Amino acid sequence: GKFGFFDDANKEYVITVPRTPYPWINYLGTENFFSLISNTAGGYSFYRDARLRRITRYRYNNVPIDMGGRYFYIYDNGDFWSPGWSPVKRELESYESRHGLGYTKIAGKRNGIKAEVTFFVPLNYNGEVQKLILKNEGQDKKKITLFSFIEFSLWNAYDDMTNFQRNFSTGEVEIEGSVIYHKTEYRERRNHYAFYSVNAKISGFDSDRDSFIGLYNGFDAPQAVVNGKSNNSVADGWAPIASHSIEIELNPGEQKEYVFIIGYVENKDEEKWESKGVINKKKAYEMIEQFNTVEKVDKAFEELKSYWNALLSKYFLESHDEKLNRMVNIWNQYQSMVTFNMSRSASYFESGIGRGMGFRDSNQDLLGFVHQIPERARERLLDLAATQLEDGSAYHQYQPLTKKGNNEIGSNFNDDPLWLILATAAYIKETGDYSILKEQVPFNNDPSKADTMFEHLTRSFYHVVNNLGPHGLPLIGRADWNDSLNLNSFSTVPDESFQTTTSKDGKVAESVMIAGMFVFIGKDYVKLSEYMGLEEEARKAQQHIDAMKEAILKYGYDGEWFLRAYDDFGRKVGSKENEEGKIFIESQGFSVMAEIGLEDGKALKALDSVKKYLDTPYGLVLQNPAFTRYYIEYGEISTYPPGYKENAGIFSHNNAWIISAETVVGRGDMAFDYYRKIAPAYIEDVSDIHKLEPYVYAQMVAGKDAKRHGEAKNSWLTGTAAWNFVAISQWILGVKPDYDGLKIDPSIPKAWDGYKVTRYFRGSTYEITVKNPNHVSKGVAKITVDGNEISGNILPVFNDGKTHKVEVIMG
Amino acid sequence: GKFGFFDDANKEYVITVPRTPYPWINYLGTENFFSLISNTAGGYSFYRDARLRRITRYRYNNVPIDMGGRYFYIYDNGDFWSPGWSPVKRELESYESRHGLGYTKIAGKRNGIKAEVTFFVPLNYNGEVQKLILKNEGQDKKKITLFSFIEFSLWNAYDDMTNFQRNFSTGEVEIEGSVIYHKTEYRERRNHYAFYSVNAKISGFDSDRDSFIGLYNGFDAPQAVVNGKSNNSVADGWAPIASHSIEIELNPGEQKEYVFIIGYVENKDEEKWESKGVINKKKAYEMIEQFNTVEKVDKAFEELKSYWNALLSKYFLESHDEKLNRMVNIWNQYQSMVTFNMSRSASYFESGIGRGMGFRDSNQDLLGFVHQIPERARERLLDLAATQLEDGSAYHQYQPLTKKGNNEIGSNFNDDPLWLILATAAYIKETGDYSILKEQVPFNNDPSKADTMFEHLTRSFYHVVNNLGPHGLPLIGRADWNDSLNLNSFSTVPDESFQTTTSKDGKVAESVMIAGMFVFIGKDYVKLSEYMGLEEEARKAQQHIDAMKEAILKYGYDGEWFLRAYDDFGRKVGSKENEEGKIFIESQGFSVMAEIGLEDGKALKALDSVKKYLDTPYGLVLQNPAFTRYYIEYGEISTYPPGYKENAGIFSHNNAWIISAETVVGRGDMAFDYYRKIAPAYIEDVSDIHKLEPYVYAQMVAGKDAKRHGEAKNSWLTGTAAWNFVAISQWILGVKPDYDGLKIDPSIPKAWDGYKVTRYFRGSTYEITVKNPNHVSKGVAKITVDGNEISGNILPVFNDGKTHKVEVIMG
């Protein structure tokens, strides 16, 4: 299972065969304009909103897969082909694809003609730039034609795919020079348009899909390309497209360069028209002139490379393992930044039709990208807090575009408020900026009810205290971290919602997972309360935390592992008494992270049980045994076939918490063994089984009860990456931000001799060399800073813009 | 422009080339199981609900068009083809398709092998039956393989096309004998499943799409078919399919027969499982045994033919024009019945994702199908009335599946309540059953507030009286008959609803069209009040009607035609003073139908203006001149490019009202000339311009301002078929149901010598021969019944199950 390899010097993944197990994609764009592009150049673009500003059309779950994108056709004396091998799918002499940081390259050769295309979105630019090089590597003079093709969307994906009865009559275009402008509904309430341009004189164009392709033809053989000539069609309803055609003559060894741009323009309502029925193209002219030569494109490309390099430079590892180096230094951080930029909107599994991301999802992503973009993290934290309700609860879905909560989805997921405390504590530990606590933040997006951010944290903390169950454990509500564990739903209707349609009062079912999370984040809440000078409130919160710990030890432990929950009948969930689902993974990680059972051997016993019952070669499953029938009292978890999704699937996100707990109990070999089973670089040798991108994490991998055990689903958009990076970089390697500074506390395999981490922290750089002469897993024998031994394991803060050498000797 | 011809003896349309200008479709099923099938066998099936019980997957607006259906592959020694020519699209020796009444036939031949398939849904059967005949017309022995293929839907089209993140892990099947059962989510909350069976022993099967087709292959060349062998794949998530493979051996001249069934089964929650994880198949066994021989299939086919013949037999014309005979006798009535069965749910332009049909559309379809199914019409009328609100208004969208109104869509369309009166009057005139007036009908689906159906009519009538505008004309509200004329919207934001998001109070803008409709239906309301004995309440309603007629004559007439409306500024709409939209079509038809301006030349002048400004060779446009820019004060009508949809498009529905109005002024030549311009059979010779089905009406044809002038959109599901049939059958030909009996009053071209109509009416048959010896257009000189001359133009009611001869002499 290889269809490629890693190129670490260029920070790329190189795909060497076009028929990957699944189309492997990449993301372009940082601020507003975004593109999804596959290894055959399939995908689509949008402007800040995949649902309401889609620029090009893409068909999900299509036959054949991934049909539709930025398609270049080389036509040579009757023959024709594509650089990406698709859609034509004629055999190429050579094919290569490269997925880099914010850009993609595709190269293809046939009959002595080579075509190389680079796709990327430049910084501060509302478009996608495609640099195309055609080269004659044959011995004879050639006369060819180049066709470009994209397919427009009508700005609203849902309407675009459902409301044909109106929108087959709305499509409009303009053609001027070498630019095709898509302007559907620009005559009416819309004030934006799209354009496709090339920086050379064209020999023909096409804008009607039925003219360029043909009604009964597909993308693999458009009639205009088959004939070797454009039809110069002007769209009038139906499906607008954009296609240029240029006739080229290449001598042997001669090459030619072209720049294609897919751009988006917004005009002011008073500057919409150049004349009656003619759109104002001034901004399009400026955009097209920005990149009308190859030198300008190359300068922008180098600027993007420098931008991504600066983003990835604050944590740099040097170890003996090149897979670990590649994961930590490039791809984990890249995925974290991409998730921040994109939310949960669009992938090849997310259709881009949703309205927002999870509140806890944003809070957890912050934990991953906080060290790369601290100020944007501060702004995101404030925006998230502003949507909280006055009672301390939060809307399940956050809308980053409007920075609002989803009123129609509701706010009864009882783990959500604690993630805000966790993210705020992480941000403060990263930056040391306590001032964020004193900011005035509205409640429910209402400035009249605004209070301090610390008050938001207090209300989140006391939301749990005010909703305890009969055993003193938090009430689970609709669901907790596991969105499919619905203990108050009791649904019997196929179309009914499992999460936001409840038939129970919700006063009995309890979550042990929320209890562990509460004990874990209470430490940070108490520490922050002491900073604000509120000592009595800190003492009271500590009392509540102690009560919760006692409740967990009295009603949350089963004998060899921690229970999962209590259902609406007051019966145990995740117990050896149950026939199925005897042990769950979620209740173990957070319980051990909170340091419950460290001295009496309960945490170690629970982790041993986790290894015994949940471990597979591809990671740890959610629960064991799997559910073989529907349990109306458990909700959506039992509606999947065994081994899939939350019915005993493998989730890297909750595997990372078991990794952290394993470090907590001081077993670094086990932590790293768990890490390698799910880390993308370590499973690249079995790509055919994994079937999805070998350079990013996926949400779920089929568990041992499934027939496709080892196959992944829902890649590229998931909170797994953030806490996986946290677990590797802070809990295993031991470079942990802390309130007073940088704490060193590795939990590593005994056989390692050492490693080096360069960390940018609070205005300075720390070059930390770890040594393991006695080959232990945990414990620091000595720390030296600038040649002087220090006391403790907290590094001093300098904030002087210089590099300080740190020597850590373990033992 | 022919790609086929009419076969009137078999009541079929025969398509002789597979590449029609657009895929031409047909509908199968009468009661609960429904199928859309194209001329290449594309389409899909569902059970009563295209949105929530879709059985097979179909992709709208796909490239290439219409890919996905019931696909049979003939594999012959390496070659392979399809009888429908699609999806393989290899050249056939012969191809034919036939669209009949409730069934479709497709025949194709290649390399001496002929395959013909008949698709239909039998009566009282929850499935689609496909009878396949293979024949060796060659000279040598042949050994071939037959593949059958369908692609399943996951029961919920919207979820099926948006929610891949969950539903790529839910697909499940069972395979037993020659049957593939699709049972996705049957394990949790669904009590229904689907199956695909063949009545012979199979040599192989496939149920995983990626195994049968291949990830990078399309429907045109599935890998299993290319290899000539099934893979026996069992679906596990992703895309479940159903495919059979049978190895056949045919001698020269020998034929073989097969029956394939796509069936739907619903089980009781207690009889769901045969054993643990095994679905109960008893009902599937009974269904499959019902049609396991060709004799049973043929018997069911003849029963369906008899059913449709009985449906079409109540109105039979015999004239000199075979196009008119074919339209009146077969296709108009067929379309009316299909619209009753299907509502507005699914076509090749309606994606099947909506949740109901229009209230006015439901009432207007009844005027077309009332003479075919009187008792079902009575039930439908009662169901529609039950959803009416207490103030007399109605929900804009009706839900026939639940017989409810759409609460979220609103009720401020001020023309809706009058259509209920119109439909009730039509039903009573058809049947003479006044008892419906005294039924107890709930208000807003609330039995506590129920009253008589006549009370519902009264509240509908007085909803207009209580919402008059400054000129004494009805307030238009959100919209009227024309849903795109929004005079209270003033929308500036995209994605915003034009019809249900108002910014003005709605106390100024008036509709002249609603005024004409009110005057037109007031006659029926007064007649019904007189029948109910409420003589005082009929005098007051007559006073209101007279006041409205005076208001129309004082503020609704522009000088040579009737005005259209007044906007929120109190300014005229549809006036010669306006720059664009000087005259509209809607305000003329209903005004003349109400008989306003008959004795002073106003109606004739308005009709002459309609002829002068709105007439094109393809029908009459909505308004002239077209709007060339957005008018915020007019709403959605201005958002289309000129000549398309409501911006000066051609709508047959409002052309029919002009036809009736032309009959009212006694100009039968003009009425028939308008009728022929839009009647399907008369435009079959220009099928390449029309581009859509030549046997059914379409909603809209591009107007003279459009570049595609003459091209149709949104065919096969409409309201135009009903009133077009009414206009031809009652207003031109003059066989009009009346309160006291059947009224004869033709308005025909002067050159016609006569014709004959056999009408089934109120329990008897009338064989009416019309003669025109003096060649007039209107006026009845004599009527003779059973050889005896009668007085007046109302035929006596017999209700005796016999045939009575009627002789009408015009003059």
Image: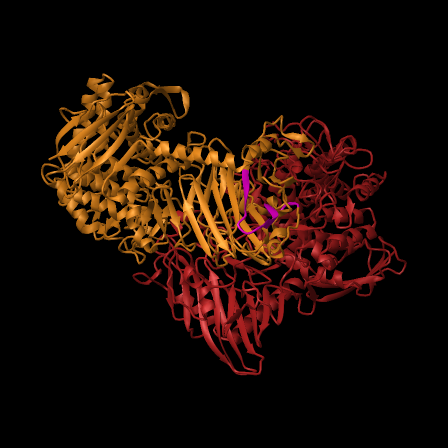
Chain colours: A red, B orange
User: In what quadrant of the picture does the C terminus of chain B appear?
Assistant: top left
Specify whether A533 is left or right of B97.
right
Residue A326 x/y as whole percent: 72, 62
Q: Which picture quadrant has residue B340?
A: top left
Q: Which picture quadrant has residue B424?
A: top left
Q: Residue at x 62, y 71 (%)?
A: A94
Q: Which residue is nearer to you in this view: B4 or A177?
A: B4
Q: Which residue is nearer to you in this view: B798 or B467?
A: B798
User: In what quadrant of the picture does the N terminus of chain B appear?
Assistant: bottom left
Residue B785 x/y as whole percent: 18, 25
Q: Which residue is nearer to you in this view: B64 or B243?
A: B243
A494 vs B794: above or below: below
Specify whether B272 is left or right of A166.
right
Toward the top, the furthest residue is: B533
Q: Which picture quadrant has residue B518?
A: top left
Residue A88 x/y as whole percent: 54, 64
Q: Is residue B260 magenta?
A: yes
- Residue A565, visible in the rendered structure: yes
> For the image shown, how many numbered marks are present on the structure?
0
**Overall secondary structure of the magenta stretch?**
strand
- Residue B398, visible in the rendered structure: no
Q: Residue at x 80, y 52 (%)?
A: A673
A369 vs A163: above or below: below
Residue B484 x/y as whole percent: 32, 44
Q: Is residue A789 magenta?
A: no
Q: Which region is colored magenta?
A: B234-262
Toward the right, the furthest residue is: A774
